[PDB]
Image (cartoon, rainbow over all chains, first blue to last red; front, side, top):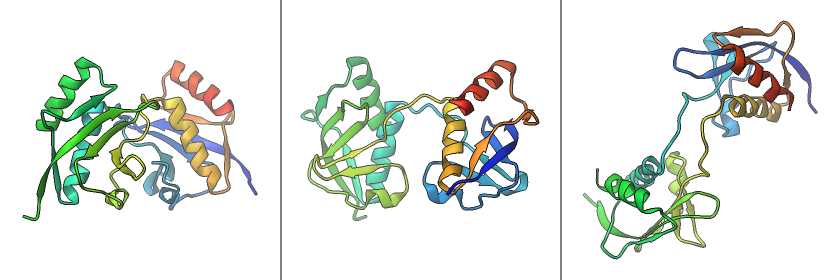
Length: 99
Length: 100
């Protein structure tokens, strides 16, 4: 049950987000799709997040931060097992878990 | 305060490239509720990330078109399509990404 529609504009804003402005439709609730697409009303555009390349280090900290929100401070031990983590990365990750 | 310190039993990057943190004892069934893009996999009892991925404008355009399509609108680029601050090459690549 679709419906074809022309895009009025494609734009990259000053923060690097890409905006697609629909020919006519509005999507105030595009967030409910859980696809990290947002709606900016002032410009009636669907847009991406600010460009982001997340390292494993940053994801590790994110995972730690989430567990912390639920009352658990995770720490690495001398017995923690590292599985399929290159040596160079392990160092970086270990530093991440502490920083 | 109620904050419990705990050992990590394992760090693992799986076959799909997600990084897994296996807590020593705690479980986090509702971790998704923190809205932080972290998930709990009960079969492996681990917190994990999504699959890694580089930033790509083409992909993001496709992602944007895909979100719109879920809400019943198939977007298409036209000859009258206005491009603001989109460099020549990116503009070509974005055009092709919208076609494929």
